[PDB]
Amino acid sequence: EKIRTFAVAIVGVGGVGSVTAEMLTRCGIGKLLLFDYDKVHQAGLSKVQAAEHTLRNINPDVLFEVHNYNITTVENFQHFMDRISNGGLEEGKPVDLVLSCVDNFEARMTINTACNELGQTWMESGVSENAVSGHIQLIIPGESACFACAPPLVVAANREGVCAASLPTTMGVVAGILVQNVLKFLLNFGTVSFYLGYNAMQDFFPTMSMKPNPQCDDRNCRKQQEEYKKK
Amino acid sequence: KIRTFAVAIVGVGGVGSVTAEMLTRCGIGKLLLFDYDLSKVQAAEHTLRNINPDVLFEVHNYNITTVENFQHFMDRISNGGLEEGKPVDLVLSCVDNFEARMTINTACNELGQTWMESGVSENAVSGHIQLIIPGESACFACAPPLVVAAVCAASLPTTMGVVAGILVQNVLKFLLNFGTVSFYLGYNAMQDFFPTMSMKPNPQCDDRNCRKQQEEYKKKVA
Ligand SMILES: Nc1ncnc2c1ncn2[C@@H]1O[C@H](COP(=O)(O)OP(=O)(O)OP(=O)(O)O)[C@@H](O)[C@H]1O
Ligand SMILES: [Zn+2]
Ligand SMILES: [Zn+2]
Image 1: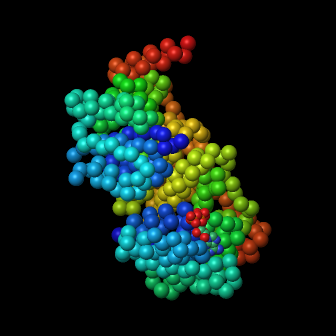
Image 2 (image 1 turned 180 degrees about the vertical axis):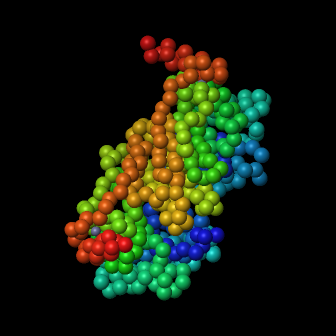
């Protein structure tokens, strides 16, 4: 029942994002907001619209809102923040969680800038190009390290058939663990991980948590931090 | 290279269906599917061939726990590989009951067949995969499961997905020979703990063939 009452924004509907959207659609999430800027049978149609069609056929009860814009532009970032602030299940209420499943540093940093301003909790996820590592990170602005608090973390791992076979499998594991964390966070059960790595070569799942950097480059991080230390 | 291997999957529900699909998408040479009550395995074969028609399929619907059907099961593990008359490369147990798992154990000890066993609890909070190399590591009869600790309308399919994903990654590492294959890998969804270990065989194991295989393994080491 309770999962129907939440909205989740997914930025990037590629490898990890699409598996994640599919899994949440099958769980019966109330609403998915999908953001991407790429185009892909649906070979040619925008990625978000193609995803929307596939997903709505999987579960017609899930409400979809899709956006095709590049969020790294100031103009489009305004629209992105409007939808994060107001795109919840009830219009005018925030989304309950944002998931970054983008593939580049600039987009991750853009999500981070928005969430620090808004005080929006989010999860950042990635699969390395080596196809044998990935991670998820939970970011609660003011309470845990934000994406800007420290430079990019890397999961330690270290021919052609190997990467081709492993990549979708690694994406599937990372998406599975990301979704389990979304459910634990929304449904309030078990313990949500703040950082969880996955080394597929060794079946190693390093976990830890990072505290915020009082000298973070993002002033809004510094601000959320001040507000957290008050409460 | 992955196209050159055959894998037998026992149990086509839950973890088994996710696992078969992932292997089908990777382009494994052949899948042999066993389950028992268009049947369950026939339905699976149909969906899977639609996903990747490069993959060959052989399905069976008999109850492998009878002695008569057990002979057919062992026959197919020994001869059902990519080239007819060759062994499958790996057997996967994705069944949700003790008798089937033990039955698979008994076959694999008699044949010297390496296999992986997988499971997810009813509660969805935990699951595991286990590699078994008869004579070299603990078989299913050697010891009971002792590793500790390792909503449902949502958690269950998610846990099954994580277990299937880690199982498949281990199948690829086994067949393609990269990274390290885990012997026991548990998953605790509540806490995000992934206990791992490996266990030697029980020299007094109840399975007569596990004992036979151990003697054989010790004999080759020296
Ligand atoms: N600034 C951005 N705004 C919106 N979407 C973005 C932005 N930057 C990256 N993305 C999207 O994030 C997604 C990440 O997907 P991923 O890298 O896992 O797959 P991929 O390598 O793009 O392969 P495929 O295109 O087959 O999915 C991509 O769809 C990409 O277009
Ligand atoms: Zn910060
Ligand atoms: Zn034994």
